[PDB]
Length: 29
Length: 46
Length: 294
Image (cartoon, rainbow over the protein chains, first blue to last red):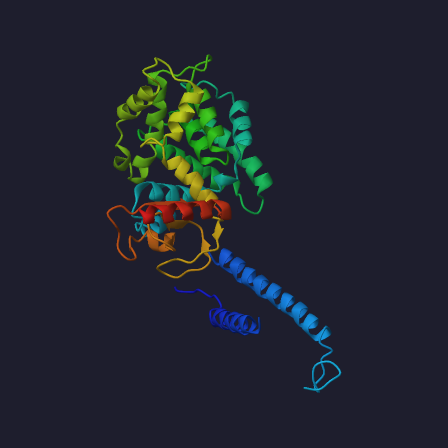
């Protein structure tokens, strides 16, 4: 009787992408 | 609340967007006044 | 109704009192299909049979005629949802359960009116005003006796299911005393004062606003995660702690009494029954940060 679904790994990979672009563009600036 | 979570997520996306836009503007400037070539700055060669 | 009550008997899991009464009464009203009845249709039906005197004795035939008048319109609106004879039998069963404990075949018009108006689909204050007009005189004034009769009719309902003692028992005297103390010891009370005292949420009448809330929140959908069973999105009742941070519980685990991280010296809780407004929840989040700062 447990049924919950929210995309979590997609959230971690999105946070990873945001993090790397933040690193890269701050380095570029 | 995932709502404001997503909201601040693409707010951060907006901030990264503006930093990219201003960086491209500065780099087009840095290319223009420099006459830049793989040989070197201007018409000379360093 | 025997199989309905057998299904009810397995739902003794509600920890609190008012929640239990509201949920069971909502289940009954949806099962009886009387939630399809509006205030206007019931009022027209009762005024059509000239059942205006509250003390008028009522035989079985008059109740049958009024119920037929209501349920004919209900079926004409709900052909695929209302069967007139079965619904008439069921509603007669319930009404004579509440107000015919003596098996005399005679009831009062006021009790039947109170039951139908409480169990119909209308605004809470509209039902309050109509019942006050029913119990008040032509001048709109209500003394101790009419209020006591109305409270007695109201308290005849929870004793039928078995949750009468949790709301002060069947003794209507404390309720009248509280109502007339809120009335500044006035000999008579008015409709506005009656509404204000009802919004004060007395012990013996909170069940009806709790019913209205659970009916409203039955279609509520909250974008939140249950902080025990991890259910996202929250559908129904959302409960947010007013002490800790990011703690939101669904009613599925709330009704079982299971508590995450333990309770506190005081564990305040707010009960969202509607999808939230971001301004309001940011304001209450600022309030809870302020509370935890101290």
